[PDB]
Length: 198
Length: 198
Image (cartoon, rainbow over all chains, first blue to last red; front, side, top):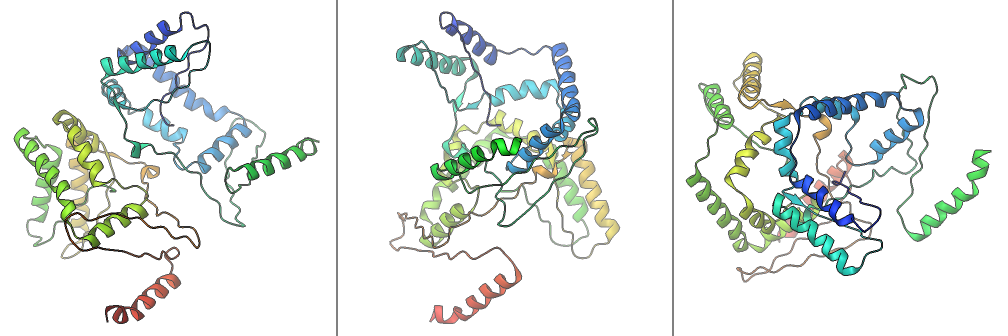
């Protein structure tokens, strides 16, 4: 929801080469129309196939949508999927790569100068082939969680058209994430874990 | 901040003709490069002339920024203005007209059928020349106001560089808009109006 995520894990011997190739395909992507149609139809089949997920998964999904400030439902994505066209996408990729921020975490059998060399390699490739420009700090917008009122109870109700079983997810909200509240919630959840199961 | 605003007022004799011509002009606009550079430069001057505004106007501006959820500053606009290019705008206009919502108010010497004819003409023209699609209701996000904490006092300080006088604006945020709160605030402001002046 904040942008792309790329992770390369494994032996560091030939890692920067493949990473460079992946960045090269990010900044030199040529879309095949047949692959585009097949993959698009597959994604449509995925959004259609979400209706066959399990009731508890639907409960976690609905609670996610309710609690997050901004969240698009799979029905909205499915409806907007028909309007996606190849010229729109080909005009959208450089529009995406035109303004970017990057947050990296390099943790492994590499040195500081090696990490700086890899990072500078990625930056130089993105600038060279994609003309990527940094983002403005005021544009670093994180999403807030909906605040429930005191003594307030809300219930969202939907139906599962596939499984003959019912699902339910009860969520009580706390103030914020501080040390004291974290240890309160974790300690209580530790006390009620096995009694809840049993 | 929510979108464009257009208001045509006057004799209704040729209002539909003029309005139709306006929609056609916004849906078939061809940009002049000279006019683009000149109007852009005049916009840069307009952004640079805010420094000569009065300190109370600077106060209302800063307070508006502070209490608005999303608000971009004159310096951010004047900095991002240097990146505005003719191809970027030429790609922005159809992107702006691709999906839209409309909220109209037709009041005066007008019949209901003529109002529906005007609205239907606007929709037909927008879909015709701009392929305008309806906007999702979840995309109709309204900005909120920063919720101040109880017994909280915050002070933002700046300096006017042109006028030799100083300004100040003191804001006691009340609760959300309801009948009781509205009449309390308006009655108190009524009591303190003339004693404030005198």
